[PDB]
Image (cartoon, rainbow over all chains, first blue to last red; front, side, top):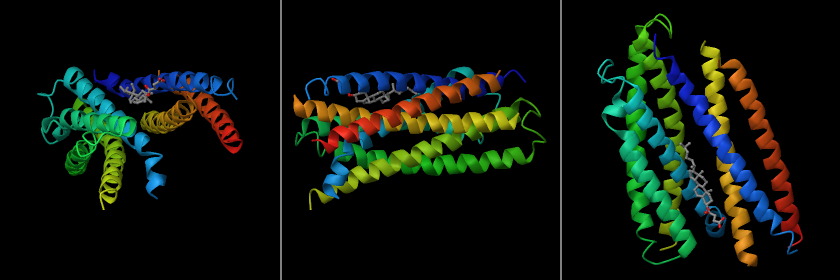
Length: 39
Length: 158
Length: 37
Length: 34
Ligand SMILES: CC(C)CCC[C@@H](C)[C@H]1CC[C@H]2[C@@H]3CC=C4C[C@@H](OC(=O)CCC(=O)O)CC[C@]4(C)[C@H]3CC[C@]12C
C-alpha cells in the first residue's frame, strides 16, 4: 500500500508517553525522596 | 464533594492539556504524512473540519488555565478558566459530534472494502477510524473533565 | 494484521491510563511537597 | 515489526505499572503517618 507507517504512529506515540512516564516516575520519586528525607 | 473535586481539579485540567497535545500530534501527522487530496472528505471529516487543531488549542488553553487557576487561585484566572472550560465543553461536544459523524462515514466507506489492506484508501480509512476512535475516547475524557470543571466553578459560585 | 493493530491500540489506551495516573500522582506529590515547604 | 515492538513495550508498560503501584503505596503510607 505505501501507507503502513501510519500504524507505526500509534506505538511511537505510546513510546513517547511511556517515556514521559519514566520522567513522571523519576520526578515523582525524587520529590518523594525529598519528602522522606525531611520526615 | 467540593473538596473531593478540588483535590483532583488540577489533574482534571492536566488531562485536558494531555488530550490537546495528543490532538496536536494527531493533527500534525495527518497534515504532514497523509496526502489528503487522495482521500475522501467524508473519510477525512476530522481533518477537513480541522478539529485536531481548534480542539487542541482550546483543550490546551482551558487545561493550562485550569492548572494556573488551581496554582494561583486568582479571581481573574477563575472566570477566565471557567469561560475557557465553557468553550472547551462546546469544542468537545462539537468534536464528539464530528467524530461520531466521521465514524459513520468511515463505516459507510469500509462497507466497500473487502479487507483492511484491500487498497490504500481502505487502509487509510481504517487508520483514520482507529484515530477517530481514540480521539473519541480522549474527547470523552476532555468533555467529562471540562463539564466537571464547569460544575465545580458553578457550584462554587452558588 | 488486525490483531496487532488492536493490541497496539489497547497498548496506547494503557499508555493514556498510565500517563493520567502518573500525572495524578505527580500533582499529588507536588502538593504534598509544596505543603511541607 | 509490530509484534516484538509491542511485546517489549507491554513489558515497559507493566514495569511502569509496577512502579506506580510501588509509589502509590508509599504515598498512602506517608499519608497514614501524617
Ligand atoms: C505528543 C504527546 C503524547 C506528548 C504530550 C504529553 C506531555 C508532554 C505532557 C502533556 C501534559 C503534561 C503535564 C502537564 C502538567 C504537569 C504539571 C507539572 O508541574 C510541575 O511543573 C512541577 C513543578 C516542580 O516540580 O517544581 C508536572 C508535569 C505535568 C504533569 C506534565 C507532564 C507532561 C505532560 C503529560
